[PDB]
Picture 1 (spheres, protein in one colour):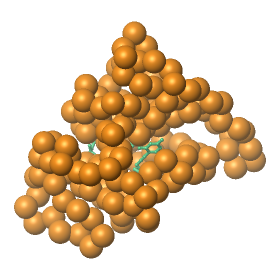
Picture 2: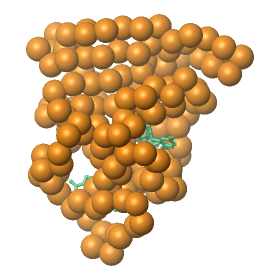
Picture 3: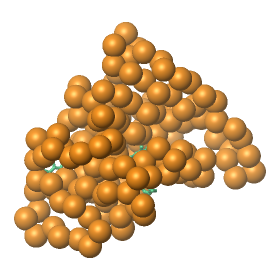
Length: 157
Ligand SMILES: NC(=O)C1=CN([C@@H]2O[C@H](COP(=O)(O)OP(=O)(O)OC[C@H]3O[C@@H](n4cnc5c(N)ncnc54)[C@H](OP(=O)(O)O)[C@@H]3O)[C@@H](O)[C@H]2O)C=CC1
Ligand SMILES: CCc1nc(N)nc(N)c1C#CCc1cc(OC)ccc1OC
């Protein structure tokens, strides 16, 4: 299975200055739950911003850099390489990867951040005409989680 995994705001903002625009522990938990034991595929800029591979799953980085060889990370140099990865593969970001893969994935796991943030990177536009809502779950608000959010699982019609 090939899935997108993304958190975007009301205007599809996903990032600002190579970082996430918001702080939301519950969404980190969501990512951990979904992708532990599976595979994340991410672009070079996203990886470098994270700074190290995420524990307990396969980390795959897409880059043109022939010198990229990082401990605990597998490198790919083409989009076509993604389709050779076994198991459940999550396209993890950032903007460039989402733009390349939105028309190809089976599935999308989207956290809608119910606010409007300043961004410089965006998830591509999509229409519910193309996607069935398999599930929609309101995020619980906390002292630690203060931005309303909704976990959507969308399946390509
Ligand atoms: N909120 C969210 O759900 C998420 C947000 N983000 C955010 O997204 C932003 C980063 O996005 P963006 O700037 O697009 O960067 P990306 O993370 O998508 O990385 C882009 C890089 O990936 C490599 N790459 C992409 N496609 C190919 C290809 N076909 N062949 C070879 N290499 C390729 C290139 O690396 P190179 O130049 O080295 O060749 C390219 O410069 C950040 O702000 C981050 O915070 C990221 C993930 C999730
Ligand atoms: C944790 C944010 C997130 N949520 C969802 N639902 N999907 C995603 N693809 C992402 C992401 C990301 C990239 C990223 C993660 C991170 O913590 C692991 C720290 C920095 C990041 O990029 C700036």
